[PDB]
Amino acid sequence: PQRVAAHITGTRGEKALGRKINSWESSRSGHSFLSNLHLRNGELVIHEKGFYYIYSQTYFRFQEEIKENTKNDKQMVQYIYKYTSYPDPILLMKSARNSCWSKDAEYGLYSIYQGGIFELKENDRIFVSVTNEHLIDMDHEASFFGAFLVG
Amino acid sequence: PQRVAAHITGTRGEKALGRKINSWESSRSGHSFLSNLHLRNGELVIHEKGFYYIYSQTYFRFQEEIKENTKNDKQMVQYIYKYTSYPDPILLMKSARNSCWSKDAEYGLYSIYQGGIFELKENDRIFVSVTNEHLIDMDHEASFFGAFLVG
Amino acid sequence: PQRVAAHITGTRGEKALGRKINSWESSRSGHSFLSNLHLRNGELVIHEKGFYYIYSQTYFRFQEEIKENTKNDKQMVQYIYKYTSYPDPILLMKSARNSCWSKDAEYGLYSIYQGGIFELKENDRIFVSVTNEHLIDMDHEASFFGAFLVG
Amino acid sequence: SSPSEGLCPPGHHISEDGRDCISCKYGQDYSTHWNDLLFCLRCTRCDSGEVELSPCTTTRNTVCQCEEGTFREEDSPEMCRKCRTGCPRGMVKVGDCTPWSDIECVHKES
Amino acid sequence: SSPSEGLCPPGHHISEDGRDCISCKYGQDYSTHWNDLLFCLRCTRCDSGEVELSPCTTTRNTVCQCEEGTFREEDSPEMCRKCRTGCPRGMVKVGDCTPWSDIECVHKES
Amino acid sequence: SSPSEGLCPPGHHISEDGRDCISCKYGQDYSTHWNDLLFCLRCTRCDSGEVELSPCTTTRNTVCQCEEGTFREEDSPEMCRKCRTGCPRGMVKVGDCTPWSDIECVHK
Ligand SMILES: [Cl-]
Ligand SMILES: [Zn+2]
């Protein structure tokens, strides 16, 4: 009960790159929980200041067809931002992958995971942003967002 | 003595997706230890209930040859499951990669890492499963499985 | 002040693979801190023996042109080593990726992240080494190295 | 309705207190074995490249199958694969594209 | 020199003690709002393949633009992409390349 | 054997309490310097496209070498790569394919 951690998952649904994932939710059926943190507009809100190991896995998955009059190269990027007592969001972590360039490519499977420790104040907000949101697979075992006090 | 964590590795020698890696082992000539958890049939057995950051890295490595009358697209997937007081295994995390589609491809190097926090009860068991098990490189520095009490 | 963790980042700068990243530094403006560990010649030095979850993300980024008198296949590998009271560095973790093989490739984005728990003695040193150092993007949100005591 | 021997029957889960068996919601979640689960497991949603062979019931998880022209197999459970539209030179169709296999092409035997 | 209401003005950050506002270093870091940050934000650095449309000042971060021949869009903020040099067969170029878009190709009638 | 000044000779490692030097097991693990290791380091196992140049001893780790026609180099230590079979247009070969290098081609 005095444990400070969170792991949230979803289901399909400004000043930051990409688009903010806001379809996260807390439910035991999707293996998600909140303990001394809460969820609001897709952001995890910090209660206790300290060092947090923050992480996210975003599953890019598509069954593409080389769309004629279109370049097909995809930049799949996951951004982890924090809103602190500053007007603009501050980027903490970013991880990227480019899709295979071959014309023979029939589909793509790109699970991106990153994590790191960042000091967070009380009432700081952390969120995940991604490019190509329409290719994200929101199955709870595939895409998630979490954090835990590491000091 | 009261620390609850584990990092296990192997060696370059049923209702779940892929195939269970059961060649992990206890001892540290390869940097693996068990502290308040144990290993049984390739599964990490929990002793203390609580929040566990579980993670695994599986190195898919192959020096392929373009085979003629067949498809060569590979789906490299890592699954992390738990056996609870329910007959069937329950998936916690999955992470996937497709191999490069180019006919010019001569080899593939695909290290897959994922992790996340999950609440585990005493006697729950966790294991790693993969597709294309024959392409996994079991060097202790490349493929591993671990967990630790977060709180 | 009794918290043992570190997360360091950089800015662009003998028996181990690849080349050691030594341009890491402690500065709040790059989201990097040191708490009960210190930095020395790009190595995180341990103060308290124990179980440490060590991790690193190295962002390989390049805008490639199919050069003339050379092959173009790239092996992007991140190595995490430890110097203990033994003359030679001991590898803890390695994670690799190969670049897309298509002749149509214009660029590559390959963020590599890995981590794991290892027992470290007082005065042990840990460092990150990579192949193709010239393709590493050292923006503090894209490439970093860190660790925390996990009991 | 009643926990026989500490467990609830398929199509149900046990309540917090452990005195009641609650029914899973049809189409939403399920349980196929006697259990002491605090909630039912979520029904799988078939992908865009798949069709629903069987619907998810309170006692049976939904069955998904690759759409015609594509197949899946043990080492490719993640994404349905496009069956080759034709054999290589000198070979001939011998087996068709099924939901679990690509087409089979054998050499020209004179 | 002085923090108004616990905040320092754009082009500055507060000191540890909270008694001084220190100027951001021109060309190195910046801050566009009144803040209580213990540091100015690092200026972005245009990667080759991008031209610096405007320098980083003490209050404004540097603005980068893709080099002639390449472009960028919302889903591709990480790397400028090469503009296609021609259109598909049965199509003719009717619009040029810009730092924000690829060439425009319509179908030919005649 | 007895631990000398708190260390054990190559080919061994020290016991838990530190009273004896236990021999590494030939073919499995090794150690090449006087150490305090509680475990001997594990012998590398050459992979599929390599040949063992010299087996692992209790004092020296296995030495692996790429198979003929393929090479490994400083930025490519994970997988043996295929050598080019010939030099580009109007260039000359001044160096052959070896397990440590691709062919080298130069100009006129
Ligand atoms: Cl690729
Ligand atoms: Zn590719």
Image (cartoon, coloured by chain):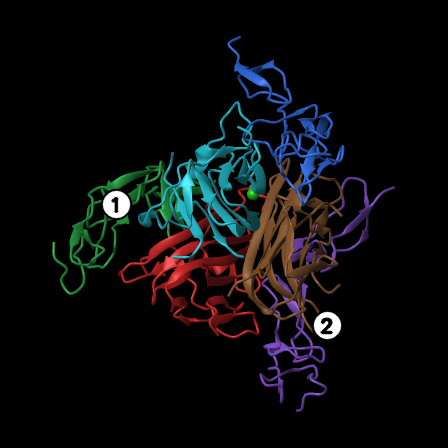
Chain colours: A cyan, B red, C brown, D green, E blue, F purple
Q: Secondary structure at mark 1?
A: loop
User: Image quadrant of residue A77?
Assistant: top right
- Check contact, mark 1 vs mark 2: CB within 8 A: no
Q: Is residue C76 visible?
A: no
Chain under disc 2? C
Is A13 on the left-hand or right-hand side of C104? left
Instruction: Give the residue at mark 1.
Output: D62
Residue A57: give x, y in percent of width and height: 47, 46
Q: Residue furthest bottom?
A: F1
| Tag 1 subunit | D
Callout 2 amino acid: Pro
Distance of mark 1 from mark 2, alpha carbons?
Answer: 58 Å
Q: Which residue is mark 2?
A: C87
Q: Work out which quarter of the rendered image holds the N terminus of chain D and state it.
A: bottom left
Which label sits on residue A47? none
Vertical relation: E9 (above or below) B29: above
